[PDB]
Image (tube, rainbow, N blue to C red; front, side, top):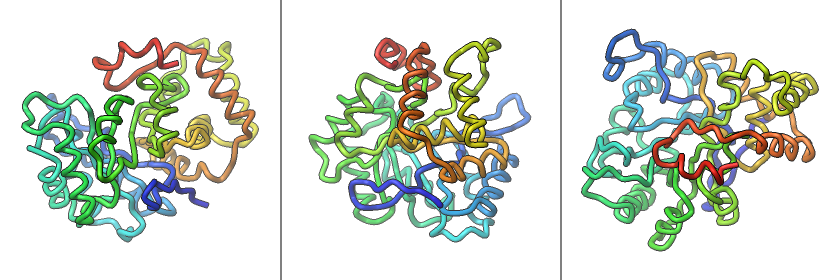
Length: 307
């Protein structure tokens, strides 16, 4: 049965996000502003066939509202069975501000609200004429109006979260960070801070370790153990790592080209890990050097405290 996290405002969010719109397949020199049929196809197929509430992770910066919008319009899936995360692009300016960005998004996607809206980065584009405080206040208004059922941030440090909390009427409910066995603190102390302050973490790129296993993986304790757990529960290595993220109290955000892996991702709650197992993945993971896929130019300086 499907599991949910409860945010600080009492609302429920599916405890895994199985469909992402950040990744696509386009046969052209210039894949930007090429519509990807294959993306819209896998999104639609996922909405139509994956059981339970389907949690989709979208963002203004991905430039794939058209693909997403086509799927939402044609899907047989009821709106109440879809949880849509969307994100204002603060790192690279595309709209003036959040209020406009969401409006533009709602129109393209043909829905009347998103379930979760995030500020995508604390590193605001120099070209914006809004700062974090004002961007947040706009999210609080999108929240009060009901156009964002829930609001939050992404890739924020402790210091960035503290800035929001100092001016917030509505406390940010979510902080989506990169998190994996090989990156257990994107920035210093973020996980402990967030989880003590009732801010749900989402983990982007949790399957970093599985992107390409080194050749000598079978000599490495981490991968050996992951295979052992895979065989014990009769589940994929991916499923084990996604469930571990959940057991850490964090919401894994994953994506795949293959409907099989999307279904598998949704089905992680068909088994459980022991506390010993959870501890051991954590510990074995921490022995690896950090692997960072996102916000690399900004947060490479924090790699020393990431593991």
